[PDB]
Image 1 (cartoon, protein in one colour):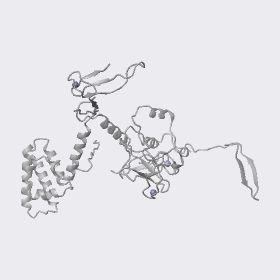
Image 2 (image 1 turned 90 degrees about the vertical axis):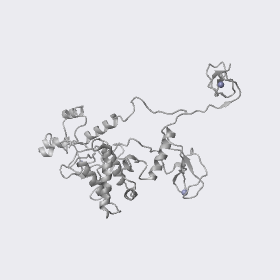
Image 3 (image 1 turned 45 degrees about the vertical axis):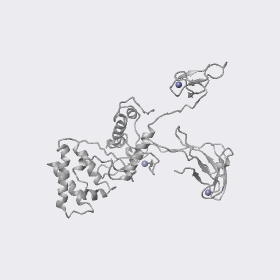
Length: 114
Length: 48
Length: 164
Length: 73
Ligand SMILES: [Zn+2]
Ligand SMILES: [Zn+2]
Ligand SMILES: [Zn+2]
């Protein structure tokens, strides 16, 4: 789904079809470089998504003082310290699942058990 | 019906210039074709 | 005779392809001709709904999940029954069945709406039925020169009123 | 940043002359690929087509209109 660029000249590659050999050949519209396509997938709309609750993590989230602290442990390092905080996505239907990030194992883990 | 993933396969039939035509026809069939019910009526809920 | 040869060839293919081999190939083509001659009894190749029931039974056989439909259709479960069944949801398989009833239960629950429950007490008395089942609720409406309204409603019958 | 820069260019003996820089200029290639025309570009920009052809530049190059500078030379 990614947007490849011509290695000779960093420009947006477009799909165009072979006339007789029946293959998608990503030809550059700037220069004459051409490349066959790995998959017949071209375009993808994705009208439904549920993604974005997790990321935005820096390696020193716990360096900020404002995050609360708890005593549930990381289930890799067993250290009782932690940093917990809710979803990083905000829709009007995002969940009350929580995200728990530790400093010792430096790992993200949740509290869902379904 | 009984397959694990319900699929539709469609093609344009006519006895270059495919992508934007097929994208517009895709957008049209998604935006226009009614299924059942009567339009300008939305979600419906049941009170006891 | 295009349909009555094509569906017969289809049943030739979907019965020879089975692990249940046809040494009783005359029995199996008897089963196929019985299947097709009850199949036409809905339509006689004169109704457009002929191909739909054929597609239902055909891809139920070629489904896999389940393959055991071939064994039960060759060892029983007779073909004039299986036009009048229309048991496409009911067969092939039962885990997908119990999935469908869980889905139907979930949808029937989720289509129900808002049911705010109106906590009651016996402090006041109704006007219509004069019962102390007052669905009371409290809120402020007027200007700053007064407290709340003392809104009232009876839940035993539906009578709304107000206290002064 | 044309003010703060200064040059350490080695000489043949190893000498390092200080040349205080004055300005910095940036160069890009242009008309390497048979660029188009503003007028017919406006006609493609206008809503004559709901979407312009993907290989329209290839069709124009096959026509030979507005060829490359190397091809013209
Ligand atoms: Zn290129
Ligand atoms: Zn850990
Ligand atoms: Zn009452």
